């Protein structure tokens, strides 16, 4: 009930959301969100997640199939509050070895009528050292909090603006924060770091994945060890860009199979949406509803190109339970949200979980795992 108690669907946060989306700068609303979470003002979802909507990627056991995508909590300043809204996992970052301010503001803009966002942030983050300290503090609180014992935390890693070879920055981050991550997400798909997406070329991508895997394996040798949720070394995911041709996607699939990567995040923002009058002026990558179809088709292609052997984390225009089921039936095992929290507020997780559960029931699925890839 929106009015009777304090909970994710509390009516006042919807009043706030309407005021924010109409009058307040996008990045300012997001900072206010994080401040409320940093001081544990936001409401909790203490509901038991349905046993039939759980999912997994190898040993990662997601209590439910909805997490928060990278770029929402870049520095891990309110990991607890975001998770407690009802999410099973969060991807902090993307982080860089040293801190950097990013591109000039304003750099985030929303189109409410199309439920779309465009951003040109440029990997703004406090730096690997400080974000590592932020994550360690969460891991210590997690061991005591019975609401977070099974929640998953991944770390997205990139490179600083003036780094020549990306692997040098990735290796630094892994040795600093890898011990506290349940998985590592390699960001070679940001459209706001010039030249980053070139690293999706098969040759460079293979070298990057293998270098990241070796550094994670070296953490074990060089060094209680795994202060994370799984108590195992982090898995390795790659986050891919949607603006690729079929031959690019096929050679990427061959690399992902050859390197035994643990999963792929499909996908990052697109630069190929010029349908939004309000974004005419603007630079950066686009998120939200206008990315949904692009991202779902991309999931179908990679699911087939990898012969269903690489688990998929879905990202792009997921707002409703039907949207999530589309991603799942396309080949995704788990979903990430971002734009949904921007346009629907604190109730995003509670609402979408209920919609998905009622849909799996309406469609005749016994559980979510049964729906993975059923479109094929
Ligand atoms: C303001 C903003 C910042 C983002 N920062 C990152 C980031 O740092 N690393 C990353 O991998 N993705 C980043 N993303 C992309 C999102 O993680 C997500 O892949 C994308 O928004 C598509 O999901 P959506 O349609 O639900 O918003 C960012 C997106 C936005 C809008
Ligand atoms: C481009 C991304 O930045 C954003 O626009 C953004 N990020 C998160 C949100 C959602 C949100 C933010 C602040 C509050 C408030 F009022 F409680 F502080 C909210 N209440 C309900 O939803 C709220 C938004 C709009
Ligand atoms: O930091 C950014 O500018 C950024 C990174 C990324 O991976 N995706 C995105 O849309 N923006």
Image (tube, helix red, strand yellow):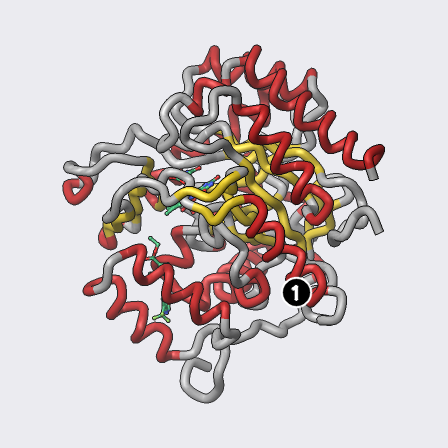
Tell me the residue at 34%/72% (across/down): 14
Picture coordinates of residue 277 (x, y %)? Answer: 15, 41
Tell me the residue at 57%/18% (across/down): 205
Picture coordinates of residue 218 (x, y %)? Answer: 78, 30
- Ligand 1 is found in which quarter of the picture? top left
Assign the C terminus to one quadrant of the image: top right
- Rendered position, 192 above or below 34: above
Residue 374 visible from this viewpoint: no
Tell me the residue at 29%/35% (across/down): 284
Residue 356 visible from this viewpoint: yes
Q: Identify the secondary structure beneath mark 1.
A: loop
Residue 149 vs residue 352, the one in the foreground: 149
Residue 97, picture quadrant: top right
Left or right of 92 on screen, residue 294? left
Picture coordinates of residue 47 (x, y %)? Answer: 63, 72
Neighbour class for label 1 at 10 Å: few (<14), some, many (≥20)?
some
Picture coordinates of residue 194 (x, y %)? Answer: 36, 25
Residue ID for mark 1: 49
Left or right of 76 on screen, residue 228? right
Tell me the residue at 55%/37% (across/down): 157
Residue 231 vs residue 168, the one in the foreground: 168
- Rendered position, 119 above or below 33: above
Number of numbered markers? 1
């Amino acid at each position: 009930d929106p009015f009777e108690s304090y909970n994710p669907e509390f009516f006042l946060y919807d009043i706030f959301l309407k005021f924010c989306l109409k009058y307040i700068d996008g990045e300012i609303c997001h900072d206010l969100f994080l401040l409320l979470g940093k001081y544990n003002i936001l409401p909790y979802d203490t509901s038991n997640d349905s046993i039939y909507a759980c999912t997994n990627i190898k040993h990662l056991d997601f209590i439910n199939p909805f997490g928060v995508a990278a770029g929402f909590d870049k520095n891990g300043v309110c990991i607890d509050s975001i998770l407690k809204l009802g999410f099973s996992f969060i991807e902090i970052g993307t982080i860089t070895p040293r801190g950097q301010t990013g591109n000039a503001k304003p750099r985030i803009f929303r189109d409410v009528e199309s439920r779309s966002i465009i951003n040109s942030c440029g990997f703004n983050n406090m730096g690997c050292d400080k974000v590592t300290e932020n994550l360690i503090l969460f891991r210590k609180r997690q061991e005591e909090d019975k609401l977070l014992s099974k929640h998953i935390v991944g770390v997205s890693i990139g490179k600083n603006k003036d780094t020549v070879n990306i692997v040098d920055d990735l290796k630094y981050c892994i040795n600093k924060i890898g011990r506290y991550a349940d998985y590592i997400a390699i960001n070679v798909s940001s459209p706001n770091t010039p030249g980053l997406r070139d690293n999706q070329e098969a040759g460079k991508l293979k070298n990057i994945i293998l270098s990241v895997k070796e550094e994670i394996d070296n953490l074990e040798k060089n060094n209680f060890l795994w202060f994370n949720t799984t108590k195992k070394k982090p898995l390795v995911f790659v986050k891919l860009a949607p603006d690729l041709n079929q031959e690019q996607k096929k050679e990427i699939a061959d690399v992902l199979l050859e390197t035994n990567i643990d999963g792929m995040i499909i996908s990052n923002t697109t630069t190929q949406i010029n349908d939004i009058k309000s974004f005419e002026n603007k630079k950066g990558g686009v998120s939200g509803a206008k990315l949904k179809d692009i991202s779902t088709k991309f999931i179908c292609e990679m699911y087939n190109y990898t012969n269903k052997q690489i688990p998929i984390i879905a990202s792009g225009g997921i707002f409703s339970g039907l949207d999530a089921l589309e991603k799942i039936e396309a080949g995704a095992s788990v979903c990430q949200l971002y734009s949904c929290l921007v346009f629907n507020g604190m109730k995003s997780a509670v609402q979408i979980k209920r919609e998905l559960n009622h849909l799996l029931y309406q469609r005749g699925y016994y559980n979510l795992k049964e729906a993975i890839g059923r479109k094929h």
